[PDB]
Amino acid sequence: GDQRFGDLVFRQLAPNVWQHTSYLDMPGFGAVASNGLIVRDGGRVLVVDTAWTDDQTAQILNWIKQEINLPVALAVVTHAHQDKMGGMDALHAAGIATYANALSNQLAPQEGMVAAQHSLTFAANGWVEPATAPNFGPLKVFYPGPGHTSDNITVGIDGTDIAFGGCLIKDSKAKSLGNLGDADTEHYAASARAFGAAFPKASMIVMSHSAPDSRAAITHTARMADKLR
Ligand SMILES: Cn1c(=O)cc(CP(=O)(O)O)c2ccccc21
Ligand SMILES: [Zn+2]
Ligand SMILES: [Zn+2]
Image (tube, rainbow, N blue to C red; front, side, top):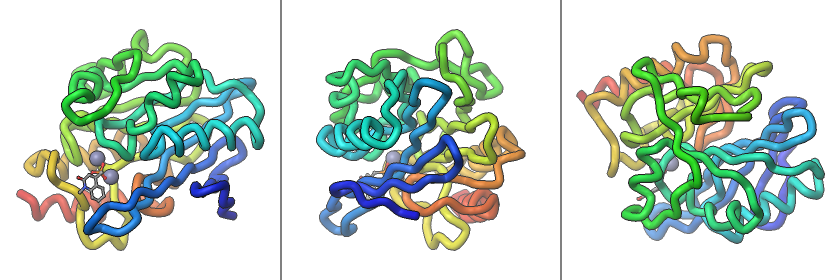
């Protein structure tokens, strides 16, 4: 199932959906995997999250060229940390339109990230304002509230059973909530539950640092975040 392609790993999740995985040595944490998504929508490809680095992100584009061979119409990145935005320059060098939460773009320079070209804004209930996410096809973008970071966003794939929680959601056996350095600990639990309520039909939950899991990832993450209060 897993396909090793250079230093990256790709896994098909559905007929039109693949997970990309890249690794970065975290001095003190080992070589940390980070996952994003690749979605074919008709004659074009949509990407969720970069890899950790520009070189790795260029390799994602190389894999897309070889395995799908359709243009990448856009990428959306899910918060202003390196695992999700570290490869922005590679997307720009490739001519790909890029999108992030307005707050992620505001934070990008101080986080050492390059901002996306376009800013998403969100209604009070968390759903993306559609005018800011043109041509997103099956991607349904939802801001669940502050959690792993204040800017974290999530993405459902219409027509599939898949929703992507990024670094907000941990797997059903996870022992911790990971890096809380930029987290909102008071609101995390509610934000995790809001993600679940936004995508009630998603039976496959994809996340940044674990293999895809059932919805028990959501309940378990929320129950763990209850202890942060
Ligand atoms: C220590 N530290 C960080 O400062 C930031 C990240 C990326 P993120 O997962 O988006 O928070 C991180 C990831 C895994 C392990 C340690 C880490
Ligand atoms: Zn993060
Ligand atoms: Zn993470």
